[PDB]
Amino acid sequence: PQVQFKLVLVGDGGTGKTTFVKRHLTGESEKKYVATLGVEVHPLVFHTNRGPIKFNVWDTAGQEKFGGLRDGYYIQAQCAIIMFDVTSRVTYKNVPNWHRDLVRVCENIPIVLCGNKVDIKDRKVKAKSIVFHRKKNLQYYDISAKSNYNFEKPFLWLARKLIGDPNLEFVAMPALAPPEVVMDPALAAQYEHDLEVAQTTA
Amino acid sequence: GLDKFKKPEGSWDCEVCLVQNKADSTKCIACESAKP
Ligand SMILES: Nc1nc2c(ncn2[C@@H]2O[C@H](COP(=O)(O)OP(=O)(O)O)[C@@H](O)[C@H]2O)c(=O)[nH]1
Ligand SMILES: [Mg+2]
Ligand SMILES: [Zn+2]
Image 1: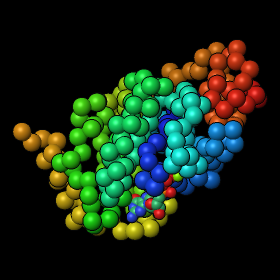
Image 2 (image 1 turned 90 degrees about the horizontal axis):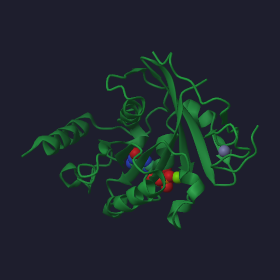
Image 3 (image 1 turned 30 degrees about the horizontal axis):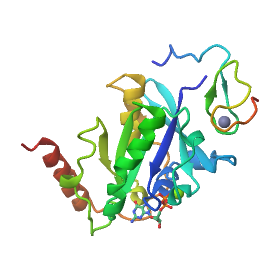
Image 4 (image 1 turned 135 degrees about the horizontal axis):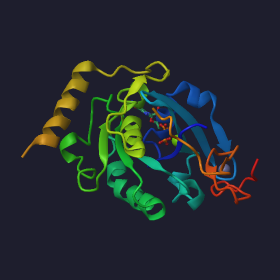
């Protein structure tokens, strides 16, 4: 009997949700297509110090471009990632709408907010502006799907909340698709610094 | 460890979308597929 969680991955079209979930190679080779709902469920195993956990990540087939997702998509979700694109302010402006839709169907499940595409130099949504998570008990991470930057962080935070073990760790990284773009180390360090300052500043 | 993990008695995993369903359910609560 495997420990597994349904994770819904939501956010505006074009933010990188499919690119992000596909980084996990076994999750892609073992994905399941759900015809009735237009979903690809990716079974993502992570190996923790207490054993394996599986996040069954629900990736849309693009329907979020045209309207809200159907109830079946959200049903029995146990956690979520809301994604936006740090190069598009519109996608960050829609984050409260995604959070609203989640909480309406799923109440207080743990949610992580992810700002994707931080590999791109001309960044528009910077750390100082990313404040939605502060007021709602959400955890925030910068991510770059195309470079695997911070890939594991949303999943570790969720796993800790779901299991109720603040000391849970991943003993190894999952096998991920090789980076397609470089995440500049100086840029990452600067963005990491900017978030730390934003989180600590009075 | 996770040695103390167990699923509810009679619960079953949907073979189409992987959602865990109740023992008395005949169809998946999410995707409506029949119980395997
Ligand atoms: N530079 C960069 N492009 C990304 C990243 N993630 C996705 N993209 C691209 O953004 C476009 C939308 O990606 P997609 O995964 O289809 O987004 P979705 O509609 O949210 O599922 C595509 O051209 C991706 O190649 C990223 O981390 N960095
Ligand atoms: Mg997609
Ligand atoms: Zn199902």
